[PDB]
Image 1 (tube, rainbow, N blue to C red):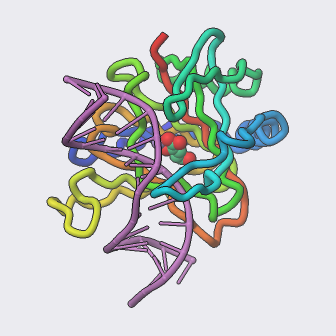
Image 2: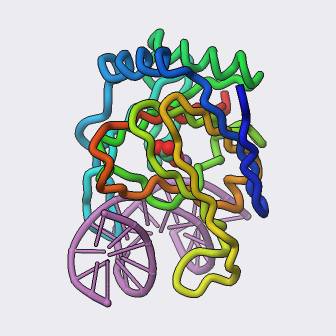
Length: 204
DNA sequence: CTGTCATCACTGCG
DNA sequence: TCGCAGTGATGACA
Ligand SMILES: O=C(O)CCC(=O)C(=O)O
Ligand SMILES: [Mn+2]
């Protein structure tokens, strides 16, 4: 197993293909059968005073007794199911990092996406990495430095682009999430679904 | 309670 | 097809 070190100013991440094709295919099939995604209010978001559907399906799973916040609201993730525990255990066995929570984002095709953002670290264990595991269609992932955004950025730090492949793990390490925003842009030629699992270590 | 700060994804272009 | 510029109500925080 080979790791690519992704390095830039205030960016430290590591990328590998963690699951081979056969295993990744099995896992994808099981995620597609079993994951229960949000419906109703949790699948809506208000942006500049207009209501939209979240442009991807989402779900959370995690340890018993954990709660988290979604926009001021206190929520409980769903209990682990075996396929998710299988993924988590492989990530932990390889990296030595442990997680108690996962956010699942399912992009039905290239029109589902997520805009430039930094992960909310407020309820995360201090200094903890985030482990991003991907199954299904490859999708382009983009890191952009915080001071290189918008119309007249103060700095011209180069963007960092990579595809996240089927069965891959991207470890995003501190201080990546302080200095960089990441996104999964629209890619209209991608017709197939992708399921991404972002494992986190939440306080408690 | 107040006031600052960061934030989410769309439309309408080019 | 890609992606820029412009669009604010809301919650975190001190
Ligand atoms: O789908 C992805 O790889 C990114 C998801 C992500 O960054 C997030 O939900 O915080
Ligand atoms: Mn993220």
